[PDB]
Image (cartoon, rainbow, N blue to C red):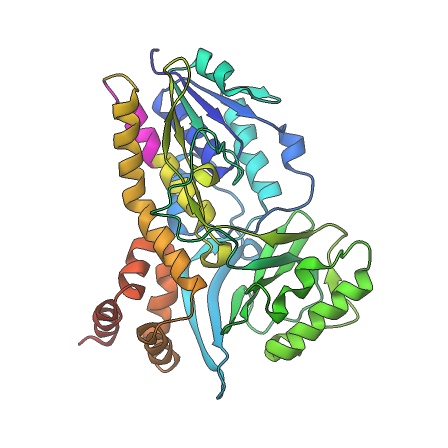
Amino acid sequence: TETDIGIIGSGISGLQLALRLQQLGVPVTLYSAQTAEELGSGRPRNFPARFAPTQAREDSLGVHAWQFDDARVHSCAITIHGEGAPLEFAGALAPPSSVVDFRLYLPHLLTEFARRGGNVRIGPVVVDEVARRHDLVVVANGDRSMRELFPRDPERSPHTTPQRILCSGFYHGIREDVPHELDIHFLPGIGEILRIPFLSRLGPAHVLAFEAVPGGPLEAPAHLDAAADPAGFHREVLRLLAAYAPSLRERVDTARFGLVAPGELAQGGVTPTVRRGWARLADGTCALAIGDAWITNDPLTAQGANLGSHTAFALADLIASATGPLDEAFCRDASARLWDHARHVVEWSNAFLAPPPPHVMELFGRAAGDKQIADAFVGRFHDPVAMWAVLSSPEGVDSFVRSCTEG
């Protein structure tokens, strides 16, 4: 037909857009730098949990898999360390979120797109070459984005350097109190420590993630070459766990503790950036950005992959129902529409990087003594808009607490 879409990048957003356009009848070509086999190898880059809305999109794409508890998180346990006793509460995540290694997930999608007749082009990409071949280019590569096509929007990008320095990897050798339960430790002015059960390509494992405030003490493991000195790395990880998350340190079977394999680790920082969602290319073909090519958030709120899955389904409906040309007016309206949802994700993600305001600290206390509140709070990780409605304003916390207390 006439609407021919060219997608660049094999992320979750690019692959789901390809699958969804294909379901809608839109001709689509995917330009991926890697093959399916290459997508299933290499060092891991991130550890995304996919909440219920993303699984529902996966349902309608006919790609739902990993339907067993080893790839699910059913409950979240939060510990806030103060100067007094640490604030502790746990709430249920119902439905569970899916914690599947993207070296299992992304090949799953790409393979199914190709098998359904999707046209897949493997190799390096020249934007103008894609623009010669399609009516619209959708860029959906990583955080590297294009940067030439989509400049950084400063009114939506309050940060310019990473707000956390990351050290995250798959580990064996941690005993588990509650199965399929996520552990978050908030260390004010220092950072966050997370332990997430996860299904990796190397089996079930523990994601031990240090989100370090830069210059603070948690930055240490992000700068150790764990391959060059495994013993030194693990010793430093255990030391920091002992210092700041002892409830986690006590569960470490030191006989088995360590990365599940050399390289199963990601270290670095992430600079939260919101870019301009559209771009006019040389020949007049326009270009839209989704996924990390458009918006980059700090992984702490775990909304990254979910936002890209949402923006893919939203952009697809716009492309598929577009009766006019896919010109700048279309792209500007599209980007505006996508930003209306993405805004809540960016502002919530940036809020969690900052010290918790008092009305947030109050909600945590209220949830520490009311299981209905803790369950309701955790359950809203499924919905970034409903979560941001609570965390933004102090009246949002109040109106939320009231609904949980039937008052």
- 80, 407: nearer the viewer: 80
SS majority, magenta: helix
Asked if residue 79 lies left or right of residue 330, the reply is right
Q: Quadrant of the N terminus?
A: top left
Residue visible at 70% across and 68% down in the picture: 237
- 145, 366: nearer the viewer: 145
Establish if 157 lies above or below 392: above
The answer to whether any part of residue 383 appears in the image is no
Question: Where is residue 161 shown, x and y percent of the image?
Answer: 51, 53
Asked if residue 20 lies left or right of residue 341, the reply is right
Q: Quadrant of the C terminus?
A: bottom left
Residue visible at 25% across and 24% down in the picture: 329
- 253, 168: nearer the viewer: 168
Question: Where is residue 303 shown, x and y percent of the image?
Answer: 43, 52
- 401, 83: nearer the viewer: 83
The answer to whether any part of residue 262 appears in the image is yes
| The stretch drawn in magenta includes residue 84 | no
| Farthest residue, direction left | 407
Asked if residue 254 lies left or right of residue 342, the reply is right
Establish if 66 lies above or below 313: below
| Farthest residue, direction bottom | 84
> What's the magenta region?
314-323
